[PDB]
Every structure is written in structure tokens, then in C-alpha cells.
Image (spheres, helix red, strand yellow):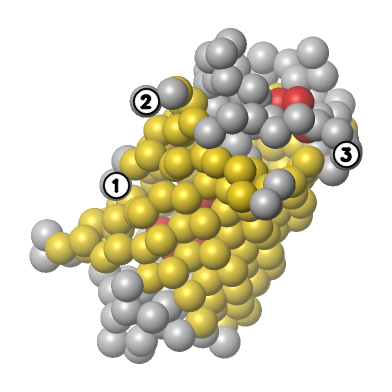
Amino acid sequence: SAIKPDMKIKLRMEGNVNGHHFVIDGDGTGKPFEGKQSMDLEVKEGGPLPFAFDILTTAFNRVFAKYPDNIQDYFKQSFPKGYSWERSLTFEDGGICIARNDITMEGDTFYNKVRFYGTNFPANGPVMQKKTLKWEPSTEKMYVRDGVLTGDVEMALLLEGNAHYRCDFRTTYKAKEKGVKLPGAHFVDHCIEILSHDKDYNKVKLYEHAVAHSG
């Protein structure tokens, strides 16, 4: 196995939300076979961010997901060459984001080149007013569409005032090496949490747990 039970994670994200530019670095570790990863993030440019940090967090690698023997593990089978993903986030108030990650591996470390672009958030909305609290746990549906592994999930951001703010995610996943076999349709249960932060979310510790299953 290319992938060891403990791996390091290095990341840089560049992006722009509603005209606001930012650069964010990450340094993390995780346990691919237990489906657990954590990361320390530090905003390097454009802080303090004028939008909810929460919109970014799922952009900060499905290799960290516990797969049973009876489902093909496309992600772990992608290494050492790696894979890329592309995601659209469609929020219920018209906000739209486009994100991508190109994932490589050198030794015991995954490198992630992330881009994140968002637009059309209303100035008076929960994202630009910083009113969000957390993503609710949920279930990604994995299937193949015209030869491309695709994951769909309807996600919910819990807002102050006990309301949710809904968002449809679609991610396409593609191995760098041709001939990695596609999996059959399945589910991935996942939960992402902000574990700690400083005053303006310039330094943040992030955690994700993810488990694949057949229903």
C-alpha cells in the first residue's frame, strides 16, 4: 500500500468571494483507513475575512474515509499519482461557489492546490453578515455519470436564530492515472467541525470524519 496509516497534509488555497481576495495555508495530519483528518489553517493574505469562514471548510480529500472491503475505494487506488476534484456549491439565496483541488503525494505527505471562487452572496445575507454556526452532518451519494464519479449532497448550514441555510453540493472526482476502475454507487456519511478559532477566524483548527457504506 502507497498510503500509510498516518499521513501528513500540506495545503494552500487561493480565492476570491464577492470580490474579496485571500490566501490560506494549512498543515494537518490524518488516518486514511480510519476516515479521520484534522488541519490547522492560517489566513496569510486578505484577513480578517469579511464572510463566514464556514463556506470554505469542505474545500480544506476523500482518501480520508473508511471504506469497507465490499466497495471499490477509488481514492486510495488513485495514489501515488493522485486525483483532482471539482465542486459546485449552490446556496438557496443565489450565492454560488466553484472550488477545485489538485491532490498529489510525496512520501508520507499529501499536497493540495485549492482554488475557491464565490459570487452573488447578498450583502445582507448570513454569509456576508457572518451569521453561520456549523454544517449539519450529512450523506454524500456517490454514482457514476457519463463515465465520471460524482458525489451529490444537500447540505444545511445552521444559522443563528435556529434557522438553516441550504446548499446543494455536486463534486466530480477524477484519478490522474487512466484505467483506475470506477466504483459502484454508494454513500459517504460525513461530519465537519471547527474545533477552535481565534477572534476573526485568522487561525482555525478543522476536523472531518467520513465513513463509506451501502445504505
Where is residue 3 drawn, in percent x and y? 75, 20
Q: Residue at x 65, y 25 (%)?
A: 73
Vertical relation: 204 (above or below) 68 = below
Q: In the displayed structure, does residue 32 sit left or right of residue 50?
A: right
Q: Residues within 10 Å of mark 2 (few under 14, many from 20)?
A: few
Q: Around disc 3, counting alpha carbons within 10 Å, would you say few (fewer than 14), some (14 to 19), or many (20 or more)?
A: few
* Farthest-out residue, left: 161
Q: Nearer the viewer, residue 169 or 205?
A: 169
Residue at disc 3, secondary structure: loop
Q: Which mark is residue 215?
A: 2
Spot occupied by residue 104 in the image (x, y as percentages of width and height): 81, 41
Q: Is residue 79 visible?
A: yes
Give the label, 1 or 3, closer to the camera: 3
Q: Quadrant of the C terminus?
A: top left
Q: What is the distance, in whole Å, between disc 2 and disc 3 at their CAs? A: 29 Å
**Three-letter code, disc 3:** Lys
Which of disc 3 and disc 2 is earlier in sequence? Answer: 3
Residue 136 has which mark?
1
Q: Identity of the amino acid at label 2?
A: Gly
Task: Residue 183 in the image: state x and y as whole percent.
Answer: 64, 30
Q: Is residue 16 left or right of residue 141?
A: right
Residue 89 located left or right of residue 11: left
Q: Quadrant of the N terminus?
A: top right
1 vs 2, front mark? 2
- Foreground residue, 189 or 161? 189
Circle 2 SS class = loop
- Residue receiving disc 3: 178
Residue at left offset 24%, top offset 57%: 158
